[PDB]
Amino acid sequence: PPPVGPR
Amino acid sequence: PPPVGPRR
Amino acid sequence: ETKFVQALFDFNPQESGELAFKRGDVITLINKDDPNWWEGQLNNRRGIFPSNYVCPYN
Amino acid sequence: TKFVQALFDFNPQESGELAFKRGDVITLINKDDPNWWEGQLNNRRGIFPSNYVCPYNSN
Image (cartoon, rainbow over all chains, first blue to last red; front, top):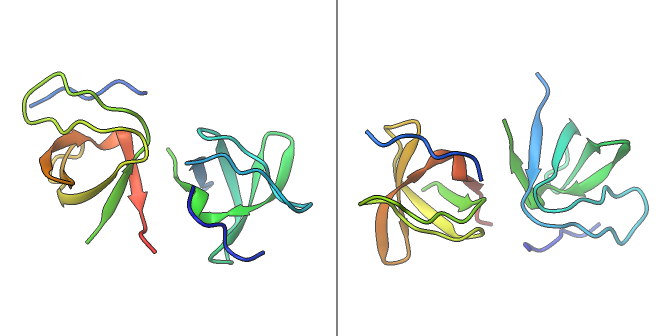
């Protein structure tokens, strides 16, 4: 998957 | 996978 | 108009309030003001998810 | 300009049809036909069903 951005 | 449309 | 987004990958939540989904699921868009975190409705569940894990649906 | 990503595996049954696997990223070349789009997938060029892909933003 693509990188999950900072929460 | 949906059906592929017909070629020309 | 109501927008729908299809999940490209599984999203396993690490924090509460995040909408869990599997690849192929179709989420109903509620909010997408944030470039990264969007809110949607998947069945009886509602929460936020990574915008890059989906794309438009029919 | 404009990249698309495969939603499902596509095994061409005809000539000029670009084969691909889910997750593949394709560069769009032409989309005159609403159903049969032309693009580039590495060193292979050809047409593919538009209902088998969706936009790939790329960073």
